[PDB]
């Protein structure tokens, strides 16, 4: 079983053994988290395009960057987007297990510019939990908003 913590800081500064990028299907530098990952690990974007609902790892030496493509809710129904978001997280979990890493830095997928204007903290975080519960990794969730940090921490505390 995994452990979970939350940090309010730039995920490009993580101290974990791998990072999950909030990637786009074209493999482009993007904005937000995706652009912060591109700035720190630009070589991880070599042939990183992957479809919505999937994850694709590009290694930077022995440091994995796991590009996870959540849906943009502006282009999906709520129910189809929800399924694709759950799927992206399941694919992250499978990659984390395959890579044998002890810890993983992970942002909340399909928030911000992919959220369709809606607050998707609970939705996205719950799909993260469901997927990562199948691993034994130390999971560190990264956010930038102080209010989201508090809500993620409270959600973590009331699972155990």
Image (spheres, grey):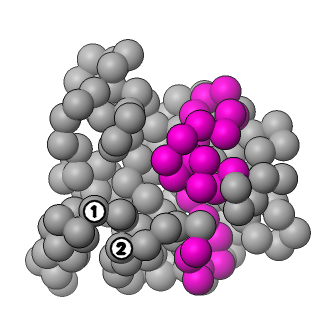
Q: Is residue 22 left or right of residue 73?
A: right
How many numbered discs?
Answer: 2
- Residue 102's place in the image compared with 93, above or below, is below
Element marked by disc 2: strand
Q: Is residue 1 above or below residue 123?
A: below
**In this view, 39 is above or below 140:** above
Pinpoint residue 1: horizontal percent, then vertical percent: 40, 80
Residue identified by numbered label 2: 8
| Percent position of residue 130, x then y | 32, 58
For image coordinates 56% across by 76% down, the residue present is 14
Residue 145, image quadrant: bottom left
The stretch of residues the image draws in magenta is 13-38
Which sits in the foreground, 36 or 21?
Answer: 36
Check disc 1 and report its element: helix, strand or loop: loop
The residue that appears at 38% across and 35% down in the rendered structure is: 113
Residue in the picture at 61% in, 29% down: 25
Residue bearing mark 1: 145
* Residue 23 place in picture, x, y as percent: 57, 42
CA separation in Å, label 1 and label 2:
7 Å
Q: Is residue 17 above or below residue 91?
A: below
The magenta stretch spans residue 27: yes
Q: Is residue 20 magenta?
A: yes
- Badge 1 local density, few (<14 within 10 Å), some, or many (20+)? few
Quadrant of the image containing the C terminus: bottom left
């Amino acid at each position: 079983a995994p452990s979970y913590r939350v940090k309010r800081m730039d995920i490009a500064k993580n101290d974990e053994e791998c990072v999950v990028n909030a990637a786009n299907p074209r493999g482009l530098p993007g904005n937000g988290v995706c652009k912060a990952v591109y700035k720190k690990w630009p070589e991880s974007f070599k042939n990183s395009a992957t479809p919505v609902g999937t994850a694709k790892t590009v290694m930077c030496g022995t440091y994995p960057v796991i590009h996870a493509v959540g849906p943009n809710f502006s282009n999906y129904s709520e129910s189809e987007g929800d399924r694709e978001l759950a799927a992206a997280y399941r694919e992250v979990a499978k990659e984390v297990t395959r890579l044998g890493v002890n810890s993983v830095a992970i942002p909340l997928l399909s928030t911000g510019v992919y959220s369709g204007g809606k607050d998707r903290l609970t939705q996205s975080l719950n799909h993260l939990f469901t997927a990562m519960d199948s691993t034994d990794a130390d999971v560190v969730i990264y956010c930038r908003d102080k209010e989201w940090e508090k809500k993620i921490s409270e959600a973590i505390q009331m699972r155990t």
